[PDB]
Image (cartoon, rainbow, N blue to C red; front, side, top):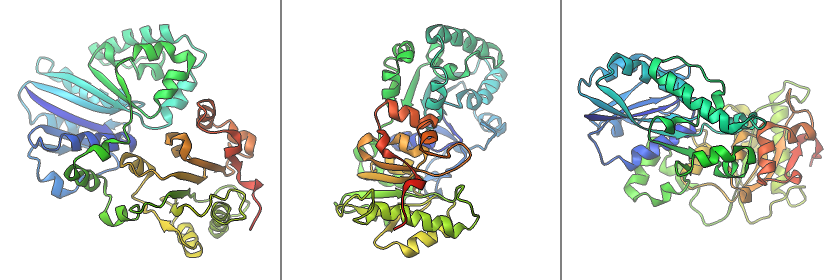
Length: 388
């Protein structure tokens, strides 16, 4: 045997969790690793410490066949420990399966760790709420078994098929919302089925790491000590969530920057409708693509600390640097937040959302409402707020 640890993700949240696993195993400089990521590349000062370390491209929802060339470097019996995105697990896994078929006596899958993409998994499960879940599970297991023996990808319920891997391999799942699985009545049979095999994504692991390992993790994810310092104060913290543009009857980007500055004022100025109080230090998390819009907001906002583009809410979560409060323009990140940290979420106009009613009907917002993460007084339509 050689064991090979293979980390696959085209998104960002599974990557960040997989890098935490790598960090926890980082003293082991021997085991072979394959990193198959879309959005993170590892610093050479880390990678030069590892003698058996490889990188593969993700293209479509799959590792390319360059992974065959990598695995061809290892002619011994191999036992593969796989780490995959839950929503895309079939597609990420398939090239590994094709490779096994080429060397069926020599290559086996040892274990699977599966991690949430994000809201996708929940939005998808919600579409299954009128099905018979118990029989959907037994079907999915038969089909998965065929898929493994032959390679053919046929699932009557692809969404539930994401969750039946334990019928074939040792598996662990890492979920953004364990409450969802435990409180949705229709999923009771899935909950029971998965018992013992899942955990909530641990935002606390960073704080439990040794200082050396914490330094390692920050270096892997590109969190400089400079930027980390912006969060070193005991003052409580509010982060405003920015956006780019929306359907506001003009194409002038500066209009949208001004309007966000007004939304921000509603949180930070004493006579705003959504005033948070003087207790919080104010941070701005602009959209990575805001460019000149973000320049504009930072030029005209007073006493505000910019969070750089490389630092996502996922990174904040994973490093235990979530702030006390988050508010501003709506996006799926709000789903990942504990309820006590959400102030108000402001929806802007697009083709789906034209008013506050449409906002309440958004797929991820519907779950949030049901799980009690927010109430309706927390959902605002951008139009309802006066200029200041």
